[PDB]
């Protein structure tokens, strides 16, 4: 709503910037500390800035909201040598088009959006066990043997009891049929019996394509026509399969593992054959309900039958499958050991299918130039546990990311805070901007700042948090990590996180950019320094910082002593950019004087924590 980035460019690139209609800061590397804070403090939109920034650290530069743009991969600093955030392609200078240039900045900038979410996420796999409002991404980096991934993802087209279908959505071309099958089924199974594995280009491309989850799986692959395989996680079977005795002989019962059953089998004048192949695929699985958690059985749709039977949990259109291709896969969940609790997905049973309702089903969702999102929601739906955060009570520690402030959750604020009162790490939208690509609403910053900050719960804006995690967990969040601080500040981040001893006023906490431009706007629109300094932060709802800690840094920490207090920075490897109980309590009084009801206990709670400490 207010937060900007400084789009710092390098020298060769500078001259053009001068053309476009956004403001240009200019340096001049001297410039004492307190210049950059008052200058930067001017610009209300994003800016461009060029010139010598030798002397500064990075955290110092990110705290200002710098984004680094050059023809070069990097740029000298005082802290370290920072990988350029946005690299302009040569020709796409050069040529000085101002628009091509700017247009260029934005893309990468949205490409940057992931970096942020990532560091965060990455912290939480270092911390939490439950995850709520998850998706394919959080899935993608989950250790399924430890993490516990929940949410309510948007559900794919299914046949069962039961139809409702479709309805149709836009989609995109994806990995070929068979591979793209593997793609959504293989998430947590430790062992995989693949019946009918053919020439194997299938399975092999899966490896050459997504190697990790290939390699943490054991693969029995049954087929007469199957080749040899050097890969030692691939016990290859050249027997053909009519029974479960062909599969049983090859399992270790002394050890509990999640096993997966994939049946994809067809022979070489009509084809009941085709049929009693699939049925068997299934039957063999069904007998072995007891060992497998799952079955991705092939299921071609008959010509000669108007409605038929089968044992199934779900039925669905396979992504990247040819339009004419009239074959859905059947998914059967089963009783048998699993790291993902699938009980919600009903215990695979007998199912009457109206061929034509299935016919239509292929007709909406199949097509070579489709499948991308289908695949997601298939994958998403199969391996996330359908549970709802605001409502769910956890015995273990949890993470609550980028789902809380979604438009579905509207008006149920109370719960949201209760979450943030005890989530390892959760996040809320706060940005008051237009603001494309993102569908959330935002919380009054003030309200966040006050409900949010607890003894255990640290309450920063996204950037603030990034800075903090850099400073506290330097190798969950490398200093070099590319992210966009502007955007990072449309987020409110909470962390189960002790206030520092000593409460050193590190950038991660103490940034407050443009608080002066912020203040005077106040006075001319709704009128009425450390005392007032506080009132603004709240009145502005430009800022989301950790009240508690900030408090505790003032009275317990500053002053104290110029001498004795830097020193306790050194040391705490902290750093800064700006270089009494009776004051603050008035701030509060005045603030809620201007806002009964529309807040905020609490306040009351906060006041009565000074008038006690
Ligand atoms: N190695 C090997 N594999 C075989 C063989 N036959 C089928 N497959 C396996 O069938 C899968 C899908 O085939 P495709 O999608 O081309 O067609 P289907 O197998 O249904 O065709 P099929 O029923 O065997 O042939 C008759 C024709 O019916 C046509 N058809 C038209 N409308 C429909 C419909 O509504 N439903 C079905 N099932 N078929 C329809 C199909 O296009 C098809 O060409 C292939 O991936 C392969 O694994 C074979 O002889 N050798
Ligand atoms: N910043 C950000 N990163 C993400 N990574 C995946 N989803 C998101 C998101 O909504 N925001
Ligand atoms: N099946 C599947 N779908 C995805 N959608 C985005 N990433 C993935 C992935 O790794 N697997």
Image (cartoon, rainbow, N blue to C red):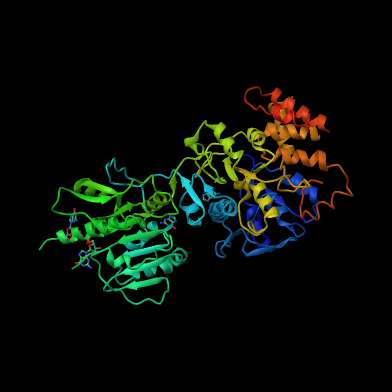
Residue that sits furthest to the left in the current view = 269
Would you identify the image quadrant in which residue 230 lies? bottom left
Q: Position of residue 355 (x, y in %)?
A: 19, 48
> Which quadrant of the render holds ligand 3?
bottom left
Would you identify the image quadrant in which residue 219 lies? bottom left
Q: Report if residue 603 is visible in the image.
A: no
Rendered position, 159 above or below 453: below
Residue that sits furthest to the front in the current view = 254
Q: Position of residue 456 (x, y in %)?
A: 67, 42
| Near-viewer residue (136 or 315) | 315
> What residue sits 75% from the left and 34% below the top?
534
| Near-viewer residue (439 or 73) | 439
Q: How many numbered dots are placed on residues in this image?
A: 0
> What residue sits 68% from the left and 61% below the top?
11
Q: Report if residue 333 is visible in the image.
A: yes
Would you say 227 lies left or right of 301 here? right
Q: Position of residue 282 (x, y in %)?
A: 26, 57
| Near-viewer residue (504 or 491) | 504
Q: In which quadrant is the N terminus drawn? A: top right
Would you identify the image quadrant in which residue 346 lies? top left
Q: In which quadrant is the C terminus drawn? A: top right
Q: Position of residue 509 (x, y in %)?
A: 72, 45
């Amino acid at each position: 709503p207010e937060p900007h980035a400084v789009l710092y460019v390098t020298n060769e690139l500078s001259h053009i910037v001068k053309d476009g209609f956004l403001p240009i800061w200019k340096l001049t590397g001297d410039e004492s500390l307190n210049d950059l804070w008052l200058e930067n403090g001017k610009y209300a939109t994003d800016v461009y800035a060029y010139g010598d920034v030798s002397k500064w650290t990075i955290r110092q530069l990110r705290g200002h909201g710098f984004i680094f743009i050059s023809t070069h991969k990097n740029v000298q600093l005082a802290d370290i040598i920072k990988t350029v955030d946005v690299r302009i392609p040569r020709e796409v200078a050069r040529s000085h088009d101002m628009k091509a240039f700017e247009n260029e900045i934005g893309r990468r900038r949205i490409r940057m959006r992931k970096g942020f979410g990532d560091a965060l996420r990455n912290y939480a796999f270092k911390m939490a066990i439950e995850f709520h409002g998850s998706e394919a991404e959080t899935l993608n980096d989950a250790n399924p043997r430890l993490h516990k991934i929940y949410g309510m993802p948007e559900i794919p087209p299914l046949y069962m009891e039961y139809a409702e279908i479709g309805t149709r959505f836009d989609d995109e071309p994806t990995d070929e049929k068979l591979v793209s099958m593997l793609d959504y089924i293989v998430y947590s199974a430790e062992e995989v019996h693949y019946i009918g594995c053919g020439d194997l280009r299938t399975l092999m491309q899966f490896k050459k394509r997504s190697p990790g989850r290939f390699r943490r799986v054991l693969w029995h692959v049954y087929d007469p026509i199957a080749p040899e395989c050097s890969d030692p996680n691939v016990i290859v079977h050249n027997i053909m399969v009519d029974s479960k005795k062909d599969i049983l002989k090859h399992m270790n019962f002394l050890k509990r593992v999640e096993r997966l059953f994939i049946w994809d089998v067809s022979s070489d004048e009509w084809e009941t054959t085709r049929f009693a192949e699939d049925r068997l695929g299934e039957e063999i699985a069904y007998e072995m309900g007891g060992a497998f958690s799952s079955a991705l059985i092939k299921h071609r749709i008959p010509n000669s039958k108007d409605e038929y039977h089968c044992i199934s949990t779900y039925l669905f259109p396979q992504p990247g499958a040819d339009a004419d291709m009239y074959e859905l896969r059947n998914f059967m969940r089963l009783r048998g050991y699993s790291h993902v609790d699938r009980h919600m997905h009903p215990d695979a049973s007998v199912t009457k299918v109206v061929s034509r309702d299935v016919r239509k089903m292929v007709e909406l969702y199949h097509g070579r130039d489709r499948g991308r999102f289908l695949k997601k929601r298939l994958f998403e739906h199969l391996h996330i546990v359908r549970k709802n955060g605001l409502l769910h009570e956890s015995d273990e520690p949890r993470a609550d990311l980028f789902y809380l402030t979604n438009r579905c959750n509207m008006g149920l604020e109370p719960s949201i805070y209760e979450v943030m009162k005890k989530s390892v790490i959760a996040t809320a939208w706060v940005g008051r901007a237009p603001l494309y690509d993102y569908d959330d609403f935002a919380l009054p910053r003030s309200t966040v700042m006050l409900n949010g900050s607890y003894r255990d719960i640290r309450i920063l804006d996204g950037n603030g948090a990034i800075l903090f995690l850099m400073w506290r967990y330097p190798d969950i969040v490398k200093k070099d990590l590319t992210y966009d601080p502007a955007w990072a500040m449309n987020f409110a981040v909470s962390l189960k996180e002790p206030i520092p001893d000593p409460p050193v006023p590190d950038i991660s906490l103490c940034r407050f950019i443009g608080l002066r431009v912020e203040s005077s706007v106040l006075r001319v629109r709704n009128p009425t320094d450390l005392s007032g300094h506080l009132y603004v932060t709240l009145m502005s709802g430009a800022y989301v910082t950790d009240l508690f800690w900030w408090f505790k840094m003032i009275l317990d920490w500053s002053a104290q002593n110029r001498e004795q207090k830097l020193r306790d920075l050194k040391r705490s490897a902290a750093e800064v950019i700006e270089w009494v109980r009776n004051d603050l309590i008035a701030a509060l009084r005045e603030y809620k004087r201007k806002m009964g009801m529309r807040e905020g206990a609490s306040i009351d709670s906060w006041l009565e924590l000074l008038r006690h400490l």
